Length: 50
Length: 107
Ligand SMILES: [Zn+2]
Ligand SMILES: [Zn+2]
Image 1 (tube, rainbow over the protein chains, first blue to last red):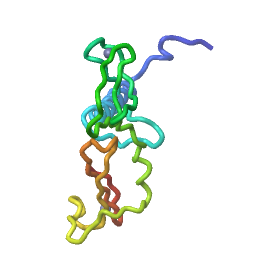
Image 2 (cartoon, helix red, strand yellow):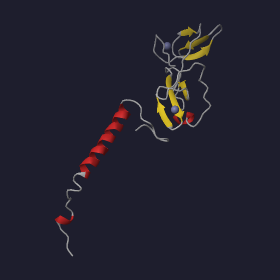
Image 3 (cartoon, each protein chain N blue to C red):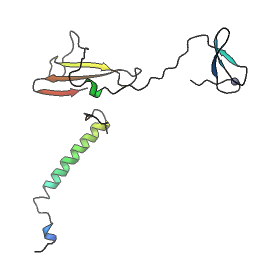
Image 4 (spheres, rainbow over the protein chains, first blue to last red):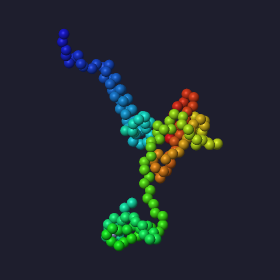
């Protein structure tokens, strides 16, 4: 019963999903940054704009 | 408001004379008769209005021949103008549309 660097290596099924998920999250965060800095942000109840 | 003596530059106090109220120095003879209306407005900060109008409030600003909202092109929407801070602010305009299978909030 052994462990190794091939037991934590990511295959091809992860290095394509990770890129798309990082791009989707970064673009939605950039959209919320742009919607806070230059106009309307639909403010959640009980907090400030930031 | 603080007002200061042109002579010595100490702080003036308001007192009453035989014909008028006066701004008067405590350390020199200078007095200034209040002849006419003088004022100083603070304009403090009012409450938030964001969570106060939501949820079918008692709005009233709707009028005959009012404009339809721009998305639905129906007059099934309220619109209002309010000061958000003190009343020296120019009033901002805001509107919300509520129709069947359609919820939106606009500016
Ligand atoms: Zn003085
Ligand atoms: Zn609507």
